[PDB]
Amino acid sequence: QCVNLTTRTQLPPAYTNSFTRGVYYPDKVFRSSVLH
Amino acid sequence: LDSYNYLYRNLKPFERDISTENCYFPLQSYGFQVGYQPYRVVVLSFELLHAPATVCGPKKSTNLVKNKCVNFNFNGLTGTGVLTESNKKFLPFQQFGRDIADTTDAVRDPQTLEILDI
Amino acid sequence: IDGYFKIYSKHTPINLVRDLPQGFSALEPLVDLPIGINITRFQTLLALHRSGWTAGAAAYYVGYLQPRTFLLKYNENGTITDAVDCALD
């Protein structure tokens, strides 16, 4: 019960900057006023 | 309870691979039929303090006390000291906080979820 | 990692029309599902506007994680306010 959409137009991928976002809490531990 | 149903074939630690590839098949069935006695062995692997605790022992809980020197055991996180109120507003995900040199300084206890300061 | 599929997220109202606004924020851990399989390829489900007819808009960015060392300054409130990639420059 799937449909094949051959109409997709394929082109080389675009690119952009990421800046500095993408940081996540490494562990489920509370830390305060500290460089880790 | 056990005496050609088992087979055996480096590999990574804890890895798992069930594959097959002088035409030889890499599988090798054992001739199940006292040094050759088959053993049904099990291994229990644990990951301590990598997450909030999920399984524990049959030890019963106890009511908590503040401003008192006590020997406490917080979900296996043993210690000694005083439990006080703290303005350390934990985000709803993390359980217990740590000071430098990796020591437990704050904890949220079961059955109340309040942020106690050790 | 080792059969645990960890999902992190954070939502932020932004103005910039297409790309990340200049700023910094950290994603919360939410949930870490015990999913014991291997993943090497993936796909994005999308909504298609049927007025078959198709449409979309908005935009989805993808980046690839690598092993790194990071220095993070946890503030008084326990919220990560800044980080440094030890191999950037």
Image: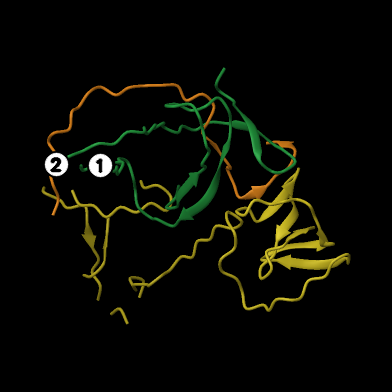
Chain colours: A orange, B yellow, C green
Is C72 rendered above or below residue B39?
above
Provide residue B30's location: percent of width, then percent of height.
25, 66
Q: Which residue is mark 2?
A: C52
Q: Nearer the viewer, residue B117 or C79?
A: C79
Q: Which mark is residue C76?
A: none
* Quadrant of image for the N terminus of chain B: bottom left
- The chain ID associated with circle 2 is C
What is the crowding at mark 1: few (fewer than 14 residues within 10 Å), some, or many (at least 20)? few
Q: Nearer the viewer, residue B85 or B9?
A: B85
- Say which element carries label 2: loop
Q: For the residue labelled by badge 1, is the local secondary structure a helix, a strand or a loop?
A: loop
Residue C39 x/y as whole percent = 34, 45
Per the image, the residue denoted by label 1 is: C48
The residue lying toward the viewer, choosing from B116 and B6, is B116
Quarter of the image holding residue B71?
Answer: bottom right
- Quadrant in the rendering for residue B73: bottom right
Q: Amino acid at mark 1?
A: Leu
Residue at 80%, 55% in the rendered image: B86
Q: Which residue appears at 68% of the width and 79% of the height?
A: B60
**CB-based contact (under 8 Å), mark 1 and mark 2:** yes
Spatial CA distance of label 1 from label 2 is 10 Å
